[PDB]
Amino acid sequence: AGADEERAETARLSSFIGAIAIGDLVKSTLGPKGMDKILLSSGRDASLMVTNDGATILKNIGVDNPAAKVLVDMSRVQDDEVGDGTTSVTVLAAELLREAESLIAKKIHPQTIIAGWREATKAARQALLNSAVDHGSDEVKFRQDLMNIAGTTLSSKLLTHHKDHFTKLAVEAVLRLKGSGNLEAIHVIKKLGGSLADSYLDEGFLLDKKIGVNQPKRIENAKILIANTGMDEKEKMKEKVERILKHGINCFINRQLIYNYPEQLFGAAGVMAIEHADFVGVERLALVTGGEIASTFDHPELVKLGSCKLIEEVMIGEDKLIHFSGVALGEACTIVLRGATQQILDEAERSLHDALCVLAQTVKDSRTVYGGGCSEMLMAHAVTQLASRTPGKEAVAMESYAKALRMLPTIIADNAGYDSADLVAQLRAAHSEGKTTAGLDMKEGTIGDMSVLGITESFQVKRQVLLSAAEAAEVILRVDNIIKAAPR
Amino acid sequence: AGADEERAETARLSSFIGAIAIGDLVKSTLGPKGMDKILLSSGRDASLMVTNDGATILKNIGVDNPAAKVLVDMSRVQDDEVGDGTTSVTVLAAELLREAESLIAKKIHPQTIIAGWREATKAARQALLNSAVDHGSDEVKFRQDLMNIAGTTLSSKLLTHHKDHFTKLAVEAVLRLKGSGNLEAIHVIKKLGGSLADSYLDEGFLLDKKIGVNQPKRIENAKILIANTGIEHAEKEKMKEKVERILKHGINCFINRQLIYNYPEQLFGAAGVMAIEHADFVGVERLALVTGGEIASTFDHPELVKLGSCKLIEEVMIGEDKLIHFSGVALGEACTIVLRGATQQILDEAERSLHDALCVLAQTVKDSRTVYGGGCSEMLMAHAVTQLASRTPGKEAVAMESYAKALRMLPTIIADNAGYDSADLVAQLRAAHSEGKTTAGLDMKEGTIGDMSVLGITESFQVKRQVLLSAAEAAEVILRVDNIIKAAPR
Amino acid sequence: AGADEERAETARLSSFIGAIAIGDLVKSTLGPKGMDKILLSSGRDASLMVTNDGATILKNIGVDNPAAKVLVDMSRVQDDEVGDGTTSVTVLAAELLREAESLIAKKIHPQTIIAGWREATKAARQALLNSAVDHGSDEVKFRQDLMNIAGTTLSSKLLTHHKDHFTKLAVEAVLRLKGSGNLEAIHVIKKLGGSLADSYLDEGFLLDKKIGVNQPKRIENAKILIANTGMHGINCFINRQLIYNYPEQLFGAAGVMAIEHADFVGVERLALVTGGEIASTFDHPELVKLGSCKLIEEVMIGEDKLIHFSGVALGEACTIVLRGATQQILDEAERSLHDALCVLAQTVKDSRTVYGGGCSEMLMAHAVTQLASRTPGKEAVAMESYAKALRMLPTIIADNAGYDSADLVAQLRAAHSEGKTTAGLDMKEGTIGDMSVLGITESFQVKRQVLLSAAEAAEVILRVDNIIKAAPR
């Protein structure tokens, strides 16, 4: 009969529906007893991607017309600057929409109500002012380094027995990277095969290619050559050898197909070459080795810089790999993971990417909050009082924000295996008293001292979630429906 | 078949329908509690776009057959000669159409009524030469620099808690700009957080790109090269020509607005030179005024056909993110504003707000005069126009009378977006204007009426001159004609 | 969802429709170019009936289910208290309902909208003192005796080509009638006589009746007898009803002229003139009867014979005979003289007026626009709807004229905002002109009663929240 026509309440509903649909899938994923999800789609999806990381699955795929893709894109900026712990930021933003039902009771102007978000700024600061932080995490630190937040990030994924040990490893990796210039040079891959450790740490960069069956096994005073252009007649062979012998070249890495004639040359010379090396691995390596200029065959000598420690092909345990290590820069390092080997193990690939940005900001912030829901209840006690102080225009919107915090305590306990109702009762009383350390103890079935557990949440996750959620939602709530955008 | 075939009541209606669709959309946008819209299209489009500015969104898409795209097109010329203010002109043109309803009651000849448009020319001249203006503005001005019109554009946006300060900053940018020629060389980008100031002012142009992972970390006494353009052994010659010419200059940086050949990329890193792939053309043109420019041609380009600014080019980090900064411009004509902002998503709306600031201020400095904002101007004129219809003879007057009631809708749109009831607001607004106070207007923050001048909100003189003439001419094309469309197909 | 129940917008519509349905039929009637309609009824009605004036037709029957009958009853009280003029009061009340569509736009409680009516008192004072009024109506009056309201009342009628002259004449009649004594006593009839003057003012009351072929032609020092019940020097006997045959033989020999089935309306006014009668049984002759004795005779005005009563001792009331240029148009003056006189009686008593041709309506409209804005929130929107109602009146006057309505609105407003109360709508001109030159004025009283009458009719919809039923099955 016509084309995309929305009026008063119907348009609001479309924004409203998108937030509720996303929340149900993500809530299971939000804690110690989180759930693993696998998605299967035709064309350029190959098979099933299992993602326990809410951010990764939402950014990758635009399932349908209803708006939510842009909100999802926003979460990624957060990921670079801290990102996770557990994915909770999307859920909290989504629940604000439910209150808009209340807003029709006023029956006047939703934009005016928006002044609540002006006071959201006031509310955002209340979390920052409130809770506390943690006492410890000085820098590096012998044992406060992990068995804390990473374990909680990890707990959602039930690989956490062999895996918590892997989670523990992640901190060591961040300590070397720690400093100005934040996140660079971390690639880490998993290998199929069993070991109790389920992981090895490499001081260098790990690849996975072989020249051929022939060629010297070990290279010394190793020099590295990287060529952008392929090797793909005798004169071409000769140019390469003449430049090569004087240098004493130990390894050649080319990001593409490699022509056969040079291959014979490298073996006799005493030089190990790599065929079709992935470009992304190469770029990281350049920062590591001091870099080099990959022009056509004039590429050797002084146009290139080559680090010279140790390059060798090492059986790590089960599957063969090639190790580049002891780089002069020292800034860039690589992590190698092993596992039980299954859906549960590929989950670790997911978890570590999350692990990688979590501690990246641990270094810069020098601030954190207590975990297990301790942070959320204290703020809720303070925010309830806020609605009364403000003028009535301000009070409705500010009060609505306060009740949102209540759901987080409920989800933590609910996944534990203990009835939610009893849990809510005891929790508020302990926070109201004034103890920041006290929180939800899932293991006990009641409440307990969070600090003894050692569960800590990044301070970084809390500042971005409050401010980002507040105006993101505010733009949509303030605005009464969008038009002349649709495709015909 | 054929084309158009319209006459009688139906013909008037197609024009009538176009005006109503656009007016509601733009209505949300005006004033302090303006509405931001995100646009979804899956017809050769990739993502939802959000445009606060009504003019920008109308320009982007021509959705259907009815006439309206040309009316929309005209508003852009207005933006360069005076800027956006808040979008209001399109709404007034649309309401002209609504009294056509009383026109079917005419039941005789609509064309005689058309005399009103000629009358309108007399009327347009009645406000342009009358109530508006200000006294002062001697060039530069220590305090009269702003705290004015930038604020009204900002007031329409919620961010004016800390943002009114940002607005103050924008005129520093205009004072430096004046000189040599018009508005063009200004670039604005918003950062993601950490400042009370919520902004920083930069010496030169700000860019965000890398050559690749390899290449020197930093350069000094940087020289800038810009190119309009991006047997096997002869390939080597291109490599060599570039190196031979390059070494003598000491070339520290190369900026190219397009794809770049792989061979040169390698060379720049060993030399100590940083190159930029697919640099934005808009960034480049701004950069050219700043560096003294050059003439872009073939590899003959390096030496004195090129002018290089020599202070400092480096990739630097502010607070947390890493950006590349061009600094030390001799010209001073063009500078860049970097907003650190007070970490909020309102900050993400800083880009939205400053862009509006950019067009408004350049015009404000050379127009040398202003009007009172917040709808102060519209209500005053409306009280006066009721009298005007009665002075003219009945054929001319009837069209003139309709034009007068058109101004009435603006008070409602300004207040309605504020969040205070629109009905209540109109009654109190009219009473204060009637008394004789030009300064008095709509105080959206209050929800009632107040003194606009204390706020500092003013409109450029130019916005009022151009819109009054433009509304009348667009309207004339529609009513005088009952059968139209255009030439070419079939 | 079963049977006849209504809420908010749907319930409102039934009230809305009743006002609109009446307006289209009545609008046609207004103006010199007005129209007369014929109607045939379903129960206890013999045939199609045609009524020229709106008040007579509205009154006879309450037909339809929607409410509107109650509104109609009010107009007759207005007619008695002043008269028909040209029907227009009903049209003004109906237009107030149209603004209700934008009423929803205010978006909150329709009942406090009613407080707008409270504001209408402000509007009511506006219709007062900031209008033209008289500034001249001293007594008799050399030029402004007429050429005014009677002419406007007259205009809606077809005959206004020679008739407008007759209408002017009717004020001479009002001046003699003038005073607090018995308003009425004015009767006029047409005569198949000759051209141009089209009417002669004369000596006394005119009546078209005869006793029979046998009876004396003229009586002097006449004695008048009026009896409620059917059948001194007695000269004439006038009875309002059937007269018994036996007395008739007697009257002829005696020298007495009697009138069979004389109209009651002629009789009551005749009584004030003579000095009154106590109309009882045959005991009626002598003192209980008051007679006047100057002269009663049946005379030919210009050709045809009729009976004239004159020389009233009392002097309180007098009558205009008129004459004319042979047609249905001519005896239309019969209806018009009576109409013109009544408006004047109010004019002498009140000693206040205004200017006609819609001059009064446009001036007030310019002033009332200010009032809406001045009043607080809720009061302002309801008050302004009333103000825009006034705008339609200028349009209706012009539309019936056969002249361009759009052009008319602009020029009309143009003359009024200047401050010249004299300028108004001249339909004969086709544009705007000086109303005073025409000489048109409206009585002060007609404007206050119309305002009170229109306001109450509007409230029947609002003072009672609901009237019918909901869902039995």
Image (cartoon, coloured by chain):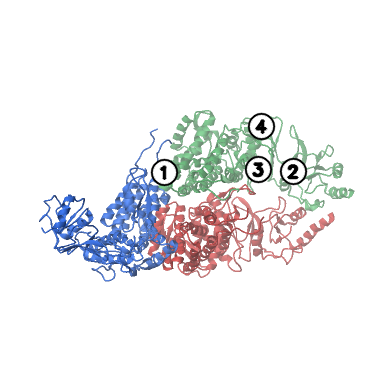
Chain colours: A green, B red, C blue
Task: Give percent across and percent down for residue A208.
Answer: 75, 38
Q: Chain of mark 3?
A: A
Which chain letter matches label 4?
A: A
> In this picture, is B120 found above or below A382?
below
Q: Quadrant of the C terminus of chain B?
A: bottom right
Mark 4 to mark 1: distance in Å?
63 Å
| Of marks 4 and 1, the one in the foreground | 1
* Proximity of marks 4 and 3: CB atoms separated by less than 8 Å: no
| Pointer 1 chain | C
Q: Which amino acid type corresponds to the residue marked 4 in the rendered image?
A: Gln
Which mark, by number, is residue A343? 4
Residue nearest the observer in this picture, C418 or A460: C418
Mark 1 lies on residue: C10
Query: Between disc 4 and disc 3, whose residue precedes?
Result: 3
Pointers 1 and 2 in contact (C-beta within 8 Å): no
Q: Residue at x 53, y 37 (%)?
A: A371
- From the viewer's perspective, tell me whether residue C139 is left or right of residue A64: left
Assess disc 3: are there few (<14), some (14-19) or many (≥20) residues with their C-alpha within 10 Å of its C-alpha.
few
Residue B164 at what x, y percent from top left? 50, 57
The residue at which mark 3 appears reads as: A176
Q: Is residue A221 visible?
A: no
Does mark 2 fall on the same chain as mark 4?
A: yes
The verdict on a common chain for dots 4 and 3 is: yes
Q: CA distance from mark 3 to mark 1?
A: 76 Å
